[PDB]
Image (cartoon, rainbow over all chains, first blue to last red; front, side):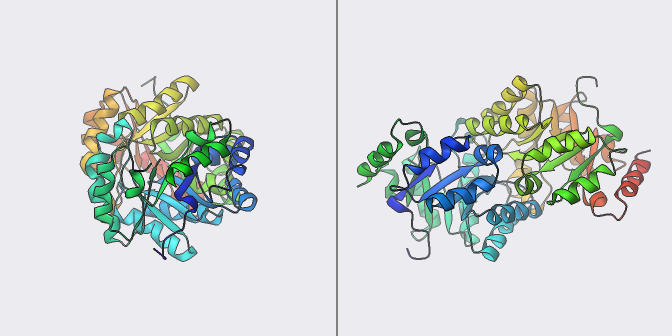
Length: 212
Length: 212
């Protein structure tokens, strides 16, 4: 679909390393295979928000800030603004704080010409307590607000088809990575499988092969 | 209670200004009235995590990192570690992601001799959708895990009393600020009331007078 982001090879790198030298090194080597890198707070809090612009300049990649924004609207607005001012192309936001908190992010994204991803669900064991039960309603909330981009877990293929049902065929959906997953998700996210490999470029190339 | 923190004058400054000069200027003036400052992402993402150490050194204050940590356990551990390495005395973490995500933070706090505050509820309109309904269970989850410190909303006195009932009289509870709030909360948090005042030192002094 034309109005949603084009992710090279349908593979996003989750660059979760906390030191700038390793992150830059492991990443530089895969820019041939990947054009979209997800960075989170472990790296940005350790090395500074300036690292976002550094990735974009050195690699020419799109940056998704995996900040799991989860505050009141006024604070959400400020987080999104600081993050986009630092150069992030997109930001991942929690839905559990409700519609006004999500809308706060959408407002800034619209102003600055950037993207908001709604995190609908999580796959770690504790997700069962509150998150799993809210996931469908969170997804519908996003749809009802015109959210275009979503993050969903891949540890359950039947969970992905359900999400895809809710958000429709036009929405952009990313999930952890893979053959089954991409029946539903537009792109898969790879972290350790790549950044802890001796030849990250090789590890990336491999995944992409299985993707064809 | 001896095993939980002493907050000077029962008043925490929420330093939500995003500019380092303004933040430092407003804060210095109230160090006489407050010894505990809450810093969030708007300031730290704008100015760098080094600002935490700067507050502690310039004012000798305790810093609570209002980062509303809400990720998977492995990522929570790293966020907490980076935050405590930067000098934060405490960190605020969401309970909605479940027990393992909270425990991840507790582990690092234990290791490094710092504190975790469990955010049990929020008071913005969107909180009604998912957070309000989870609040009591989140509070009980914290108690069951030995969490000592809690953040609760003050827009409803009767909500504070319920929280206090769950966490018991020994736990430390902080809430927005005021007279009846302190019947339940150990300390109140003041933000704009202070930092957007012509005489912050005055605005602070006044609040403390009401606290008697």
